[PDB]
Length: 265
Ligand SMILES: Cn1cc(Nc2nc(NC3CCCCC3)c3c(C#N)c[nH]c3n2)cn1
Image 1 (cartoon, rainbow, N blue to C red):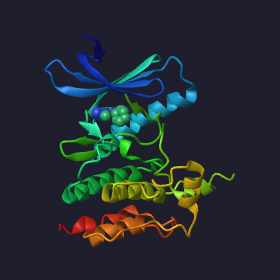
Image 2 (cartoon, rainbow, N blue to C red; image 1 turned 90 degrees about the vertical axis):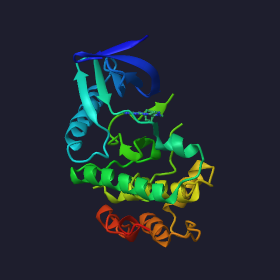
Image 3 (tube, helix red, strand yellow; image 1 turned 135 degrees about the vertical axis):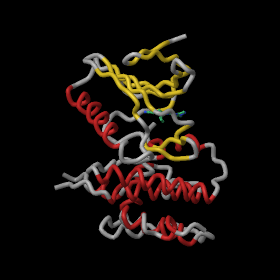
Image 4 (tube, rainbow, N blue to C red; image 1 turned 120 degrees about the vertical axis):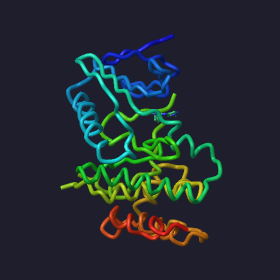
């Protein structure tokens, strides 16, 4: 019977979906038994640097949603010095958890999920965000669509051990300290997700030891395996996305003109 009020509406807590730093996300119902997700952030312990991360998420979320419905909706929010409440579109489940239920992936549904991810990542790029750490967890399934929930700025949360299987080569090499943030590095992480959606595993998921995994990502003569597949366009998408040179990696605008997106067979 736990409750939350936001602006002038009361919401009943069905369950806590997840949590992270000082944040928690709940599945809730409004006055009329309509379902929502509410993110709660406890701002009491919060340095002025995290405070600004949460403020930035809210502004972009509020701006970015006029421009695409593949971004999760933020309906209303309340922020004070002590807390934040965000009332949002509630997803059936995140893509990481839905992929780990290692079930069949329909080819047409994988194609349409890919379109969804490209559109969402495209619109954040048009407003100057590079997410930089995309993962399946960042996408939610809602009415047969994928919708992005993070812009990669605020504290990332876990359902109620991070991952590295999606990290792009530029991120590793650009640790040895003009360390630019290229839109190309989101293509790599999208490429890894589609790979996982194609072949049931991350490119370098086999390398269970993690220092050696980091080297494979950055080593040119470590070949990624692209087993031949009936969808020849899909195999090609995965090849152009997982090129180690970001300059030669395919771009999002190119990916939207690619036969895999554009020819419906
Ligand atoms: C597993 N699962 C997820 C849902 N639905 C859902 N999860 C959300 N966050 C989850 C928090 C843990 C990590 C994965 C996302 C949000 C959300 C934010 N932030 C805004 N709407 C949401 N809907 C149902 N089951």
